[PDB]
Length: 101
Length: 101
Image 1 (cartoon, rainbow over the protein chains, first blue to last red):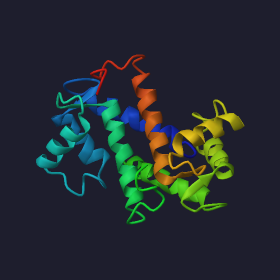
Image 2 (image 1 turned 90 degrees about the vertical axis):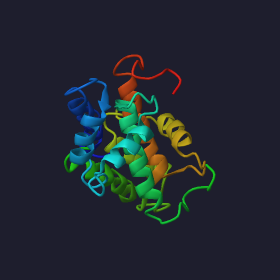
Image 3 (image 1 turned 120 degrees about the vertical axis):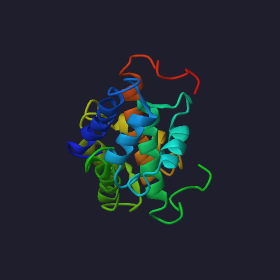
Image 4 (image 1 turned 135 degrees about the vertical axis):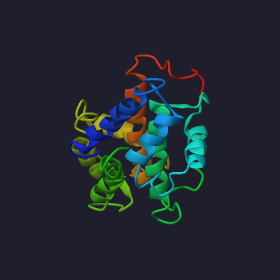
């Protein structure tokens, strides 16, 4: 959250429907659209490793509905996990955590 | 995720340490800093209802460590929940979901 950046994380939700509604589902990212969205919208995250295996595993990670198309929520939860992991690993070890939660 | 917007959700993590490290913990938002961050960084979300009760409840929601200071992760998980809820309620009813997950 922030200035217009807050509303821009909301725009990241919109980023989803931008790639989703190109092919396959308009509410879910099939591997094809998932690839493009990851490569293009996560240069840092996925651009670190944009291999088919990565997309395949990532899909199975996010796509909890396991239809092999990632929904807005599964998409956002991914980004969620990103900010989380980047954070707790920013300390190197989650010390802000009760280490149980 | 997106263009620089992706890396900007990463900047939202940085948004956190901006407000956190003003007073209290540098890795956790005490009610004071939480208020300012919510009001200022979530005009849409919290600006809809920036009351002390809101902050108090929100804190207890995010602050899972329940020390009454929201950590980066609890902060991001909040934003996560935002994008999630805004999304599943964007349909009005989570139809993209297996309604069980």
